[PDB]
Length: 93
Length: 94
Length: 9
Image (tube, rainbow over all chains, first blue to last red; front, side):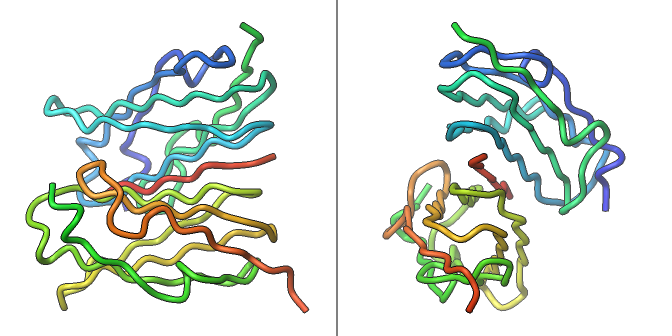
């Protein structure tokens, strides 16, 4: 359990540009024990990086090379968090 | 992190079938402290489950719906463990 | 559609 207690937000969950790191934050502090899963799906391969910060927050960045619409999934203990999956338009540079 | 001290293995790191759980284990007992990252990349999205067992092992299962070539990466403190990334052909049923 | 799916723990 816990997913309903998790929150995510940031520019990378709203809009992005091809070849530019799209960044957002996840806060799971109130959710208790668990695994976070992040997925990005759309017209090209995503490179996803993750930073577990000492400050109650988790940072995520992804880069995709092709413009188009992408879905970003954030799950806690195998369940979508509020507002996931997110649909993000990725613009040409 | 002692990623070089981590081992993984199992059928899910070799071959899989579309829509069927692909399973493998990770042993991080000798590695010390660290976080694990398990990534699956390919023609469709993986559902990933993880079991921190009492017996010194970590059980991983993933399912992907589409046939094709997938890359399975296992990183400990952000370094690839030995033999990662694994290329896994996932066949279409029949 | 191609996808990258990551699990962290």
